[PDB]
Amino acid sequence: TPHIGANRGDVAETILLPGDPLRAKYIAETFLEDVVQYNNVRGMLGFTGTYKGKKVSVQGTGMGVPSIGIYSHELITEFGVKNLIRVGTAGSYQEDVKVRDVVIAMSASTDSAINKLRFNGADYAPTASSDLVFKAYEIAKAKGLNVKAGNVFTSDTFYGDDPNAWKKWAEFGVLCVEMETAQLYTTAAKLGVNALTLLTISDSFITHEVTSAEERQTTFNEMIEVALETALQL
Amino acid sequence: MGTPHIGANRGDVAETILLPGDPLRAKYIAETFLEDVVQYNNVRGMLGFTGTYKGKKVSVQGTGMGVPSIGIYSHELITEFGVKNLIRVGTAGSYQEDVKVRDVVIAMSASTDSAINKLRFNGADYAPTASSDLVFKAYEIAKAKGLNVKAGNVFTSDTFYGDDPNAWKKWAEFGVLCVEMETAQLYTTAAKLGVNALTLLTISDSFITHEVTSAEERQTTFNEMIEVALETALQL
Amino acid sequence: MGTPHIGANRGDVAETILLPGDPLRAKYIAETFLEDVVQYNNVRGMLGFTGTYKGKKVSVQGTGMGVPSIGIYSHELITEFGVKNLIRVGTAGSYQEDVKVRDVVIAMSASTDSAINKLRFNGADYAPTASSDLVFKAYEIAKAKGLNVKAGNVFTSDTFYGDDPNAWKKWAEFGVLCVEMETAQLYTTAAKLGVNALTLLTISDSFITHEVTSAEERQTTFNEMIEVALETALQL
Amino acid sequence: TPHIGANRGDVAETILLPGDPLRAKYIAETFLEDVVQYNNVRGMLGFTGTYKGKKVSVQGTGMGVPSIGIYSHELITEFGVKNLIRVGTAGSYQEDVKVRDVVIAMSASTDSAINKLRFNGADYAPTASSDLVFKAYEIAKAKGLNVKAGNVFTSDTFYGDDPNAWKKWAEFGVLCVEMETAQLYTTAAKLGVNALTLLTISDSFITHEVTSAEERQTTFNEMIEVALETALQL
Amino acid sequence: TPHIGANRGDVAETILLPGDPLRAKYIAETFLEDVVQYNNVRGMLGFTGTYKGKKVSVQGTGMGVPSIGIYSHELITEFGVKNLIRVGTAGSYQEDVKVRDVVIAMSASTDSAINKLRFNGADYAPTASSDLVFKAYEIAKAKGLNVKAGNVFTSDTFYGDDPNAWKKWAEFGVLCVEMETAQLYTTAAKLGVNALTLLTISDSFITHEVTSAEERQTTFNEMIEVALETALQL
Amino acid sequence: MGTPHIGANRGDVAETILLPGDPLRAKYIAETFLEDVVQYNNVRGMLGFTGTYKGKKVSVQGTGMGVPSIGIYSHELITEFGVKNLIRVGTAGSYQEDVKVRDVVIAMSASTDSAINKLRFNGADYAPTASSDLVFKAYEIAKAKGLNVKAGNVFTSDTFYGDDPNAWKKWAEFGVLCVEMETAQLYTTAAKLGVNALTLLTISDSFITHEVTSAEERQTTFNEMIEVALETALQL
């Protein structure tokens, strides 16, 4: 409510969640029919339309655990959302994981304290909904995409103090780093709904390639198609 | 051209910047208080503007909500665009009976439940702290404006919707004035990079009372805060 | 010859291994499902066997209970004996009403109260995660076998007899399927060493219901799990 | 009571708190009139007198968070003290911060666990009373002292294992290291009273200058004058 | 019960606890008369017999804090065991501590989280029963053994990532590393019974000597004799 | 001459030192038990003395209260003045019914809520431990003196006035004998620097009973403890 200026009914049961509200705009204009914009509070654009006849929503979450914490909670509790598919970007930690590859997050490691606080310092592993993982994987394979499914690192920090810090995570099989998933999976689990993160590799700690701002906003089409086809099967 | 989060050139951003959380509030500040306004950023809709206030160049830009979001923007602004003075202008919820709605709070420091510094200092407690020159200038301006100003510790929360309704009380017992979501990061980043930072906050609600205020009332108080921030900007 | 915990030579262990906690369960699996069985380990009574399943070499070995115990065995098996695929086959207690006794759980990941990774990552939260190729193969086999299969997060407990009877509930609220004592270590070690790991679990009891099952019933379900693990082994 | 051998009434509402009881003695003999010694328990000297007609107290706290924890608590709860002004010494972490400079602590970073324990591992920032900060700053400026006001580090450890450990703190703007303030500010906040720390730089991690024991006890007059003038305005 | 397949009465009041069940077998066959095997669940052999006329038990615990946590709890609560003497192996952290030396653990440092969780992150020091320490020390000295008594490190990890990690512990006087004692001492203290760990040095971080599997199982006789003589006096 | 906290020369301090928390107790010990006493320290009023006991040189010095205070004094004494044996002689509050007022406790080890070692060992649990030679000598002396002596774990508290009246109980359930404020630091420092340390404690009050004792009674028991410490000193 304080953050989404709309009524229950305005948002579909399944929603795609880019971090960038302008990417939500792009998805809505490019892939959906009969689009209605239901939110402009804080510029966090949210749209509802149809994809091949099925109602779907798309809305920006902003960057970081706390921002997506706010939007995922409100979407679930106040708008009755049941399936949440993050479509985001991430920096590769693996030579095997290339700029513009698509990755499924089975789980999310994190340096956020959100769960450390709640479990008295133990290690909760935020985990994807298996059904969504399986469906998204199958759709991807049927499309010719060599999609990997594994652990991603959700960081609070884009500009770390130590340029070599990523290497410890990569040694333990972490595919890439992004900034939202540990929170999305935690909240989905807590509230009894379903969540999946798909990512497009936008930067690389191996080769140091950086995609442009325009490229991230309007050209990562493969992940969007996977997410939409996934939504269609839910 | 720019950074992956700010699509502008060096020179497009003034040396002093105001930092509302909401990019629509940046647009409002720019339209309301600045002359000859140019928009330098639209990446991710994170509106940023540059204009003059009483003849002096000043910028204003949304940061998004939360420590990680402002961490990205403050870092890029300082290292890529040469920003020297960063003044957050936000809203907060009061934890104290004598911190009333429509009061202005100056953050001397920020407590937090974010893990950003716990990681950095091997589990020790770093206290993110405001630039004193900015605290002193802002206080004297606010006072002379006749405003009800408090200066103290604020709580930078990582979690808006927490498990425990009463958890704020522990912080309130230890004198914390109010809760917001950005300041510990702003102060840490400015300290690391050797620049100047200040957070000003209008009290928009109270965990203690349930006083209601009109939109006109809220606008007037917000404008007062912005004036304090801009008159501060003038003296740097 | 060997390591201080496995008294065998390189070559004695197949590239894929099943890992019951109980070495008497390793003996049972070997006798029941494997041909031309050779025992390669008796050090500390930690029985390990190598035989063929449908003509393919496969090993099976007890790990002991707990993160430190499986930490020793998995490390030695991988680094000294060249094991590439490690499939734990265990029992677990259900934390969920729809995770019923005699169900099979595939661990996609493992939460834990062990400090092994807290130490490694400076207090951050590493999520030990299964090899997806093994998760996908095992799921499809179990499904086609008509089994009631769930795939999700399991809790690797350091303490069987804890101070607090209700402590599991916090984990259950956050979707944890069941509790066991080895998986976070198995997944972390396999990830570090660049090999493949999977945990399969039969639900032996419930924290929610108190359903009773016969030994024949328990044997049948256990055999089904082993078949899934061995049919998975076949495709690697 | 177990630690201060005196009755309510014997201590003034405003008190100066050096760590060194012999420095309390010095302040009392040098700056106060009509001095009465109210405490000698454990040799922790405490005096009450007048400064320009206003009643003030001065008492040693001992070194370290736990010692000042004891004395600040007893002073507030049993003796009705309302304003607590620590006048201490500290080692510089900044080239800008010279031996014999005076510093105001706006806040205190710490490696003490006192607050980690209480806030479930979150980061409480012990903070000075703004009124005292402003008054002390103004008095200092009117005296010709270039006083800095910023973050100080309260350590449990004088002799650290790592000779380079201080450098991380200095990178993040920490002015100097002392051993009391995080506790004084925490207790003052908890009990609803007012606190300020003034420090004289007695050692330097930059130049390695060390002042003598005599110098710390009887020659740091500038901070004492600021504190007394501050008390006078309260 | 789930882990020990026997009835109250089958186990004596004093028990020796090697980690290795085959070492329990060795002790029982070599030192005890009238031996009965009371446990074979999970192959964790347990025996009861007499040593010089006094009933004693010996049982394997398995390796690691969680495994001994299980067996020590069941032994105490369900079988009425009152004295628990671990007879284990450990790797030396001190040039002074040689392969085949015998060590008494007065206390156990640990990297286990078992107590961090329980004491809100404070530092509980698991400590031996003084009576058993004194008796075992005296017996050892009367045998000609130069026995050391000090702090041992209970680790969850045999194969650490950092080959130099042990050096910090050795600097602070840690004698050797093993994998059970912090748990045994914690549980004994909690349940109000008595515990002692004796160790034989089986590996050395100084010289890199490694004893064989056979040697650990059947040749560490000196510690066994000390433990048995200790039991006899209880 | 000296250190910033001890105003004396090398040679002024004996190789064995007794360490009361209270410097007035150091003065009392020196006057009561030592011959040919010289005061070597008055810095910060932290009285230190050197005299002979039965012809042997021994020192005695106040440490102040708390881990940080004794951290300074023990470090300087060892590294600058060549002290080899450090024996704290203090008071403590009992956590146990069979640890009665006027009993003597020998600290085998010290639990703590200080963060000194949590920082040092990356969040692991170091157990500060007494020198066994000193534990054994002191126990045998105390026993032969007919004293009621206990040897075990003590709790080194960082906070005298804690938030929670019942918090000691957790420690009491896990066998902790009593609470004091210095020992974890003393034992850690002596271990680091390769020297010998022991804490002896007279039980001055009880968290369990509320027994009252006369000053004469308290003096007698304290003198007994000092005798144990000094007879121990004699044999080093």
Image: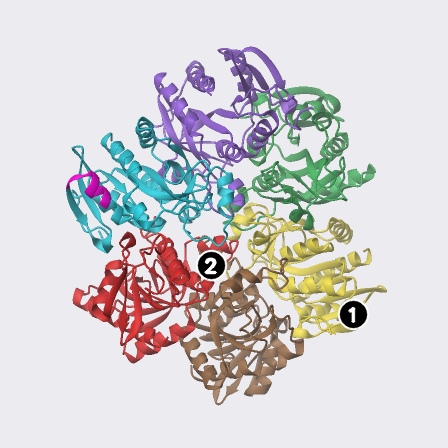
Chain colours: A green, B purple, C yellow, D cyan, E brown, F red
Residue pictured at 59% horizontal, 53% vertical: C120
Q: Quadrant of residue E1?
A: bottom right
**Residue D11 magenta-drawn?**
no
Q: Looking at the rendered structure, which numbered label has been put on residue C12? A: 1
Q: Is residue A141 above or below residue E10?
A: above
- The crowd level at tag 2 (other Cα within 10 Å; few <14, some 14-19, many 20+) is few
Residue F22 point in image, percent of width and height:
27, 58
* Residue at mark 1: chain: C
Amino acid type at mark 1: Asp
Callout in the foreground (1, 2): 1
Residue pictured at 47% horizontal, 62% vertical: F192
Q: Is residue C178 left or right of residue D61?
A: right
Mark 1 and mark 2: Cα distance apart in space: 43 Å
Q: Which residue is mark 2?
A: C163
Q: Nearer the viewer, residue C137 or F40?
A: F40
Q: Is residue E226 above or below residue F48?
A: below
Chain part drawn in magenta: D26-34
> Which secondary structure, mark 1?
loop
Quadrant where the C terminus of chain F is found in the figure: bottom left
Q: Nearer the viewer, residue A60 or C93?
A: A60
> Which secondary structure, mark 2?
loop
Residue pictured at 24% horizontal, 31% vertical: D234
Residue F160 point in image, percent of width and height:
32, 53
Residue E126 point in image, percent of width and height:
45, 65
Q: Is residue E232 above or below residue B234?
A: below
Q: Nearer the viewer, residue E21 or F29?
A: F29
Residue C213 point in image, percent of width and height:
63, 62
